[PDB]
Amino acid sequence: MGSSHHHHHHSSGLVPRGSHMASKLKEAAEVTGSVSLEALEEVQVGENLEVGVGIDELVNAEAFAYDFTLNYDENAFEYVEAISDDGVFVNAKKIEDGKVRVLVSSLTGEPLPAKEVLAKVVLRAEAKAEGSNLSVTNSSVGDGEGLVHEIAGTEKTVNIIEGTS
Image 1 (cartoon, rainbow, N blue to C red):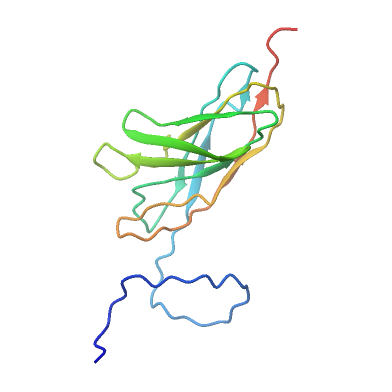
Image 2 (image 1 turned 30 degrees about the vertical axis):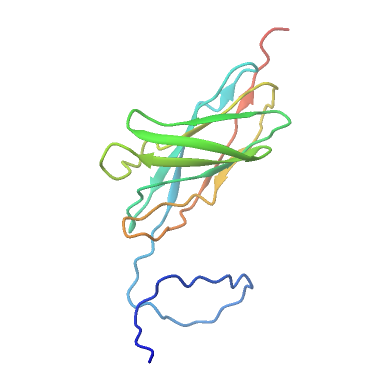
């Protein structure tokens, strides 16, 4: 007839903004979600930088895979390859100029340690760009259950210093 209760796969868009005041999900388990920006913030043309954007705060979610998307400048900088620590695995994939995706995952056995280097994206300084403001938004996290708690974000900048003269 039509015996159901669970939901296999039923996702929708609903882009349009505008919402009312109504609570459907009892209780509250929303995470703060925050990115950890740690780097020297200074490179020199012909060199590479390593800005490990990890977690600054994540309460109410078990981030197993944190894939972020940094936004740099192709005219000045040049994406190369993402890195990780001596336990977590990282892999970036150039999707656009001055902007590429990164795939992070803890291949250590334990959840994301957070508050440390979760993933660093190296942008080849093949051309100076003093003050080339960069940022990592849409930073998501793979909870232990399966849902992804879109975490906050943070901005950064790096000064490319000319080599010779």
